[PDB]
Image (tube, rainbow over all chains, first blue to last red; front, side):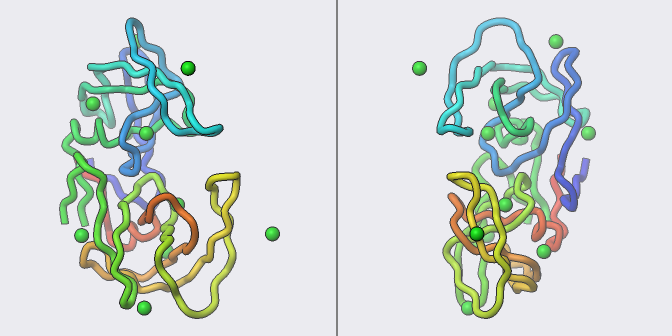
Length: 99
Length: 99
Ligand SMILES: [Cl-]
Ligand SMILES: [Cl-]
Ligand SMILES: [Cl-]
Ligand SMILES: [Cl-]
Ligand SMILES: [Cl-]
Ligand SMILES: [Cl-]
Ligand SMILES: [Cl-]
Ligand SMILES: [Cl-]
Ligand SMILES: [Cl-]
Ligand SMILES: [Cl-]
């Protein structure tokens, strides 16, 4: 799609059977979602959040659909003020900012 | 331009004689710059930053060039971890996210 920016760029995402929403955030390096579960192994990671650092789970090679486009990449699961799609997945999408 | 996202989307900006850089941040509502001065009146505004709230100065109808494109809009001046161009100015640019 072509997404304008007069409102927050919130899109529908889907991971397996879990339909959610998230912000397309060009100011975020990584993707962080609070309201999803995944099975299997994961690696701990620290991100910055309230109180200094927050521990999240890093899941690799996750299939995720963003605004109807399927990609595969890393998803961080843990506390976040908003679900955010970061540059790691926007690169998979081939997304660009255009003006 | 057409800006890819495999690195942080940092662009050159210019306000009067003040040439700087800033991140194009679709996760930011407003534009916040730390390393610029402007003359004249301004209105105080609180934003979220380290320690809860940070006081910045709100300047209106500021002419600013972003990646070579001139626009006019509101610029917040104060502490910020990175200079950020937010959606308020990206809308003026007619910027879109495309995939
Ligand atoms: Cl599932
Ligand atoms: Cl992030
Ligand atoms: Cl620990
Ligand atoms: Cl959508
Ligand atoms: Cl990835
Ligand atoms: Cl100047
Ligand atoms: Cl902001
Ligand atoms: Cl006060
Ligand atoms: Cl530039
Ligand atoms: Cl504005």
